[PDB]
Length: 397
Ligand SMILES: N[C@@H](Cc1c[nH]c2ccccc12)C(=O)O
Image (cartoon, rainbow, N blue to C red; front, side, top):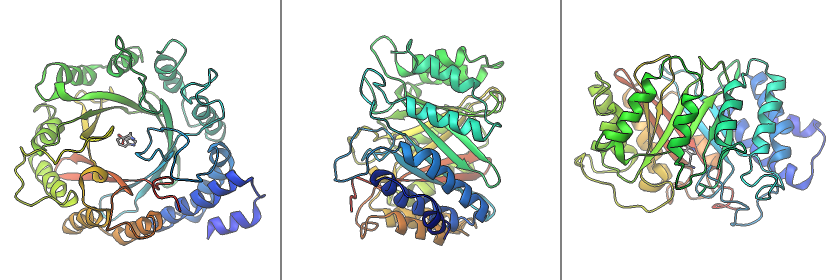
């Protein structure tokens, strides 16, 4: 084991740092091993974890109660893994998002816990010069700086994507809302001041959000960027709705019909939706889901409005934790879909990863491990991603 070797030879850590090391290291290491990552990349990932992430995770969990109301997950776990299914039986992509913390969190010196993520990004910029911080600094200044202004629990976090051979970094900004400045207002002004050459996709999304009947029901809340050249980065605007019928999801995926030639992709999406969510196969698409009242309940989407494209791209997130019956049932639904379409070469590796992450004896009894199933429509096929919560506090061992 890579983690066993590193833990055996790297210098020992404080109580909190050692807890985070001996918890995250095995999790990330198992996920990467099941995805058949090369040994060098597992070493690199765990060395990054030991050097730049573990020292900034703050106190270790010691009870069911979290030290913050972090927006990363529902139990405020500050770490979220993700497992992207690659078509053609290729190796899955492993990513993880983290919101680092400091003792100044909540104080006047960092009221929204922003400096640790900035520090992490700059450290990574020292090790990987390929990363570009132009758009990072621009959107940070626009959305979280002293000129920026109700909070969702966090205002920023970062994500590492191990893309087999190189590392990519992503930044999520969650603006603070005021009666005069909605999150969407701030995001739109930030993108307009970003310096993009072709704002056709942003204007399409704005028209859909403002004038369309169902598009008016989406509440923008988050913006994600890639730390690459601004011409090569995506601009992902996340939007939530209390509506949950599959008809609504179907229309949002098309952006009110702006996107065409997706009927087969949408039929496969409906099949996967009912399988993962445990619904009856004859569920009318206009039926709403049984009501779940939560901060992150309802249907979630993201629009990619990156200038390279004139038409925006939509990714939908099936909220497994809120509407499925249990983690094993949803996992088998997703896995059966993948097997029916010849894309399930890594299903058993995924199940071993789930069993690694799951609180002892709760996969078939509760939800929570799998937060989202992300679906995108690529021509006739689906691009799928599983999002995973280690549940440090909801499942405190
Ligand atoms: N925790 C928030 C934000 C979030 C974290 N990871 C996500 C992945 C997809 C969509 C949203 C999120 C939520 O569940 O909504």
